[PDB]
Image (tube, rainbow over all chains, first blue to last red; front, top):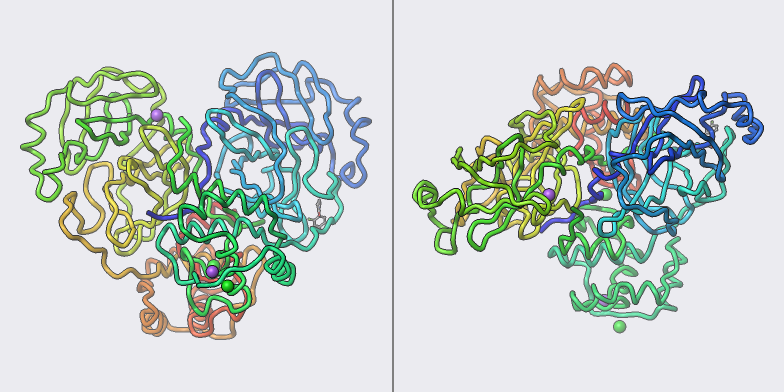
Length: 306
Length: 301
Ligand SMILES: O=C1CCC(=O)N1c1ccc(F)cc1F
Ligand SMILES: [Cl-]
Ligand SMILES: [Cl-]
Ligand code: NA
Ligand code: NA
């Protein structure tokens, strides 16, 4: 029993974290095979960051301008190039701890584990969702740039996020490992507002199923609804639209619990319109939207990653 | 900026997780140097659940009755002994991935990370606290016994918890790594119930300080309180008493924010009285009590 916000075991990624220094700037890099990946803004001074020309800033750098340390051992950089917003430092040694891995770009609403790092040393792990507005509600201090986000499939690490910057509201923006930003952001010191965010409806439903599995049932009711009717409710409450694919993905949980998705949708409609009336669900007084259907099934089934 | 329930990176503990089998029972063990630690109830049969005599069950076992699998490798058991409620299997290989480590018994209110495991393979990592009633609110399925809780200081792993059982309310009970249970619980299936649980007051205050550090002040007020009046109020909400130890521990956070500890207590008193009135604090609509003062300083720096 029990339901917790759970990250993937982080060991496979810890073995890949290194420290990258360029000038007066130190941040984190990801060492896989013989390449270290890090944010391209490592090469900027603070005035550069005001309006950077990254290709021009880079031409002026030699390989020896990039100090890379894996633990206590220096790595020799032998090449350097940019892919979108990610700098790629070719090194003379392949990481012997390289796991089976892929670079994947995730969709808003999907969750992943963040390994927060400083000076190349992992400091904490936590679970995030890519918000509909393409930010993440992370916890990062100065020095955390280059920390990465990931999922694990079987023994394969799917890297999906590299941390680049914080927005004025205190939420976070970054790229995939091919350097493409999530969201309408640019790597430049300018204030850049996140758009108004919405709630991830399919994930709220998954969490309500998690609640039921764990014996928390007070919000169930006799009613059902239609997609069209429910989606008018969702739009009114700044929830994301629920699609038929969302319904299909929740199929397993509907069959396991005896609560059809539209049946559960009628529970959510009543919760939106009436509130919780002083009650909680899985210990929360808010409707939680950072568990995916897969997260719920995996945690209520005990899948492992040795 | 930001504030998350954050666990320690789990890799140092992942390298120690093994599978222990005895009879038809499989659970997890912790392999450190040449010893594997696991719950002693791995030797129980279906008839031994209510009143097992562990000394009598153990004397009947040979080293080769214990199967210990590390990855795809069988380890050889060359000795066994019982320490309180934990079995120690001596094996013929020192774990080459053994981190710097210690065993530390914790007090209620302390937090730690849990690496949930099944069949010797890690599943997920999350953050827990030792509740005042000596249980933890974990996420554990059948097969998770032997999963451990830990903190990491510098690069030294402090192991503080080994999972043994789930109580009828769905909360969890286990031991330190010397095999002594937290709380009044025993490794028998006789009826046991956790005490009424209470809120960890010092941790709530730490978390309110985190909220101020991250830029939120809406819940403060112009008032203060005596320590005794605060405790008289807070216990009516099933909050733990706040001690002078707790007030002293909150000194650093008070100094950083400029809010005296008893002034923060006055804020808490008002929040218990008023609710949040539709607002949130660090993204929560309830008061959070599983961050310690030490956690807050480490995360907000
Ligand atoms: O430097 C950056 C990159 C992203 C962004 O929005 N900012 C920023 C600028 C000015 C501020 F006052 C606060 C900020 F977060
Ligand atoms: Cl109906
Ligand atoms: Cl909440
Ligand atoms: Na219903
Ligand atoms: Na293992």
